[PDB]
Image (cartoon, coloured by chain):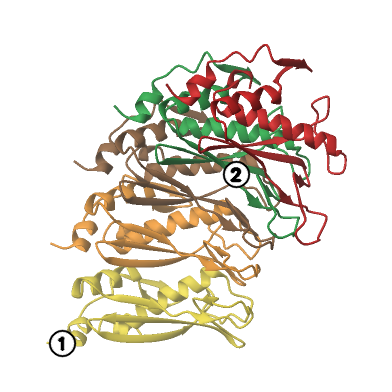
Chain colours: A red, B green, C brown, D orange, E yellow
Amino acid sequence: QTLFEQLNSKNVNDHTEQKNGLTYLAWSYAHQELKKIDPNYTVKVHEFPHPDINTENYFVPYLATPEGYFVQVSVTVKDSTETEWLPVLDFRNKSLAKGSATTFDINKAQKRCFVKASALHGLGLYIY
Amino acid sequence: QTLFEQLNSKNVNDHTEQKNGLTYLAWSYAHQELKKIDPNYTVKVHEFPHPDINTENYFVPYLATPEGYFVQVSVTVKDSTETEWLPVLDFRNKSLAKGSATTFDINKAQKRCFVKASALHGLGLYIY
Amino acid sequence: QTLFEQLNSKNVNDHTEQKNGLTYLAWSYAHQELKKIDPNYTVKVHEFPHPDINTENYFVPYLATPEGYFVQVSVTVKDSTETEWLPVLDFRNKSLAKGSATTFDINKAQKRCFVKASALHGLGLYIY
Amino acid sequence: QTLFEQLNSKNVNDHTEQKNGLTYLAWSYAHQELKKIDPNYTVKVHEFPHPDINTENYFVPYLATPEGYFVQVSVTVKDSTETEWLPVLDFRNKSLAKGSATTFDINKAQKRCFVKASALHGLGLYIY
Amino acid sequence: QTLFEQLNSKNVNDHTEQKNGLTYLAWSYAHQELKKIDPNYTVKVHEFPHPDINTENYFVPYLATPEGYFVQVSVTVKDSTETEWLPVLDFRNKSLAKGSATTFDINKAQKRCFVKASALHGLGLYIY
C-alpha cells in the first residue's frame, strides 16, 4: 500500500492520556512505531537566535517573540520531512507571555510538537 | 477529468464546525484528502522579518504590521502552488491590534489559512 | 470567438449581494469560472515598502500613503495580465485615513480588487 | 478608413451621466469599445515619487505638488500611445489642496483620466 | 501648396468662445484638424524640476519661478516642432503669484498653450 494509509490505519487510543479533556498519545509510543517502520529516522528540533541576548553564536532551542513562544520540530521518515510549529502553553492550556515561561514548559511543548509532526504521517492523525 | 473538478465535486459538509454562525472544514480532513490524491505535497508557512526586533537573522512565522497581523500559507499539490493571506482574528471574529495577539491566536490563523488555500484547489470551495 | 466576448456574454446576476445599494459578484464564483476557462491562471497581490517602518526587507501587502490606503491585484489568464487599483473603504463605503484601518478591511479590499480585475476580462463587466 | 475617423463617428450619448451639468461617458463602455477594435491594448497609470515620504523605492500612483494633485494615464491601442494629465477635483468640481484629498478622490480622477485619454482617439471626442 | 498656407486658409471663427472679450478656439477642434492632416502627431508637455521640493527625480509639469508660473507645450506635425511658452493666469486674465495657483489653473493654461502652438502652424494664426 503506502506509508500514510498503513500508519493511518492503527489504533493509538489505548496509549492516550485525558488531561484538560484533550487526548494525547505519549511520545514513547510514537518513537517505537516509527522506529519499527524505519530503523533510521531523524528528529530535529530547530534552534533560533534569541531577541534579548546579543552574544555571537548563541542559539536557544525555541523562538521567543514579543507576542509569546514558539517551537519547531522536523521529523524525517524514509526521506520525507514533516515540519510543525506549536505555541508553548500553561498546564491549563493558556498562552505564556514573554518572561513568564520556564524551561520545563518548553520541553513539554517540544515533546508535544514531536507527536503532532508524526501525526502528519498517518500515525494517530484522527486525534488532531 | 481534472484536479479542480474532481476536488470541487466532494461533500465536506459532514466534517464542519458551526462557530459564530460560520462553517469551517477541519484541517485534519484536508490533510488526508490531498495526501490521498498526491502522496508527496508541500505546505509552507512564510516567515517575515519582525518590525520591532533588530537582531540579525530573526524571522517570525507571521507578519506584524502597524495596522494588525497577517499570515501566509503556500500549498503545493502536483507542481501547482496556491498562496493565501488572512488576518489574525479574535474568537469573536474581531481584529487584533499590534501588541494584543497571543501565539495561540497566530497558530489558529495559520491552520485556518491552510484549509482556505486548499479550497483554492477544488476541495470545499463552496464553503468560502 | 474570443475570450472577452465569451466571458462578457454570461449572467453573474444570480451570484450577487446587494450591500449599500451596490451589486457585488462573490470571488468564489469568479475563481471557478476563470479556473474552468484556463486550468492554470495566476493571481498576484502586489507588496509595497511601508512608509513608517524602516527595517530592511519589510514589505506589507498594501500601499499606505499619507492620503489613505491602496491595494493592487494582477490577474493573468492565458498569458494576458490585467492590473487593478482600489481604495480601502469602510463598511459604509467611506475612506479610511492613515492609522484608522484594520487588517480585516485590507483583506476585504483585496478580495474586491480581484473580482474587479477579473471584470477587466469579459466576466461580469456590466456590474462595474 | 482610419482609427480616428471610425472611432470619432460613434454615438456615446446614450451611455452618459449628467452630473454638475457636465457630460461623462462611463469607463465600462470605453473599456469594451477599444477591447473590440483591438483585443490586446494597454492602460498604464504612471507612478511618481512622493514629496513628503523619503523611504527608498516608495512610488504612489498620483503626483502630489505643493499646488495640488495630478494624475496621468497612458492608453496604447495598436502601437499608438496617448498620454493625458488631469487635476484631482471635489464632487463640486473644485480643486483639492495638499492634505485635503482622500484615496477615493484619486481613484475617481484616475478613471476619468482614462476615458479622456481614450477620447484622444476618435471615441467620444465631441464630449470634451 | 504647403502646410502653412493650407492650414492658414481655414475659418476657425465658428468654433470660438468670447470670454473676457478675447477669442479662443477650443482644443477639441485643433486636435481633430491636425489629426486629419497627419494621423500620427505628437504633443509633449515639458516637465521641469521644482524649486521648493528637493526630493530626487521629482518633476512637475509646469515651471514655478519666484516671479510666477510658466508652461511649455511642443507640438510636432510631420517632423516639424513648434514650442510655445505661456504665463498661468486667473479667470480675469491677471497673473498668479508663487503659492496662489491651483492645479485647475495649470491645466487650463496647458490646454491654451496647445492651441497657440498649433497656431504657429497655419491653423487659426489670425486669432493670436
Q: Amino acid at mark 2?
A: Ile
Residue at 65% x, 63% y is C56
Q: Where does label 2 land, which residue?
A: C106
Give the x, y percent position of residue A86.
70, 35
Numbered disc 1: secondary structure:
loop
Q: Residues within 10 Å of mark 2 (few under 14, many from 20)?
A: many
**Which residue is pictured at 77% across the width and 43% down the height?**
A67
Quadrant location of the N terminus of chain A in the rendered image: top left
Q: Is residue D40 above or below residue B35?
A: below
Q: Amino acid at mark 1?
A: Thr
Residues at discs 2 and 1 both on one chain: no
Which of the two residues, D4 or E14, is positioned nearer the viewer here? D4
Secondary structure of residue under mark 2: helix
State left or right for residue C62 relative to residue C122: right
- Circle 2 chain: C
Q: Residue furthest front?
A: A39
Q: Residue C30, position in %: x, y?
A: 40, 34
Q: CA distance from mark 2 to mark 1?
A: 60 Å
Identify residue for label 1.
E2
